[PDB]
Every structure is written in C-alpha cells, then in structure tokens.
Image 1 (spheres, rainbow, N blue to C red):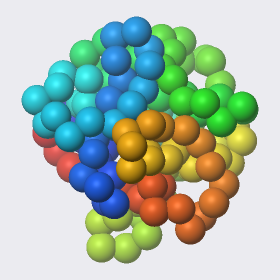
Image 2 (image 1 turned 60 degrees about the vertical axis):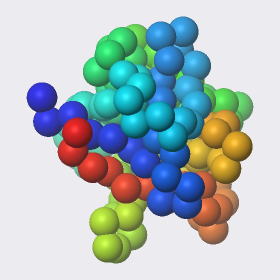
Image 3 (image 1 turned 90 degrees about the vertical axis):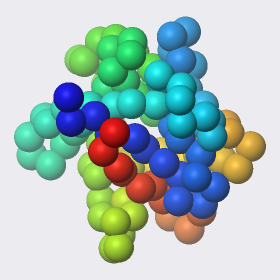
Image 4 (image 1 turned 180 degrees about the horizontal axis):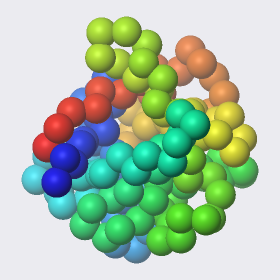
Amino acid sequence: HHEVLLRSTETGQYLRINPDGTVDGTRDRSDPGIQYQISPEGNGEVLLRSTETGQYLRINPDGTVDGTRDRSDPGIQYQISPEGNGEVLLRSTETGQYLRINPDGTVDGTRDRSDPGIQYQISPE
C-alpha cells in the first residue's frame, strides 16, 4: 500500500497513533499503529494518515499531539523537509511547530529547531 514508518533518528522509537487517538512513541515494530500513508495535498503539503485506524497526525496550537479522523481539521498539514542523508523534519503548516518525539516516548510540538526529537527517518513498510 506504499505505507511508511516514521522513526525517531535519536532513539529509534516509532510514532504511533493509538485507536483512542492518542499519539506516542514505541520501539514495538510489530504495533499496527505505526504504519502511515503519506497523503499528498499539493503545494508541498502532506497529511500523515495512520493506516490501522484512518486517523491523521495533528499538532494542536497548544503544542499537544493527537489523531483526528477529519481531513479538514487543521493542524494536519505537514511539510516533509529533508535535512540530508535521509533524515527529515516534520513541520506542521498551521503553526510552524515541528513534530517532536521525546526520549520518554511522549510526543508533542516544538519550535526548537535544535531539539534531537524532531529528526525522523521515513522508511517503507
């Protein structure tokens, strides 16, 4: 299905959207909530849709991260920005916040371009 995994370059943790719409990080490569489809929006924007539950990764204005079913719900548009050597940043267009996965497996938004938790590998399933 051309699914991809979104993996922290820092810790190797995978971004997971859970059936309850919560989002966190896990090392469990077998978890069904870590597969995504990149949804082209055009103009350099994409949505990141969890395949198991059809939810889009959302970064909320308050800096919290969760999932949503509704593609018009803002906060779900991203710019995938290559850094080099196959590492990328995932920048939410609405607010300009980067998607951050922290070493403890919590996931939130940040503007700190230097934070080690905003770098990802995107790999084919």
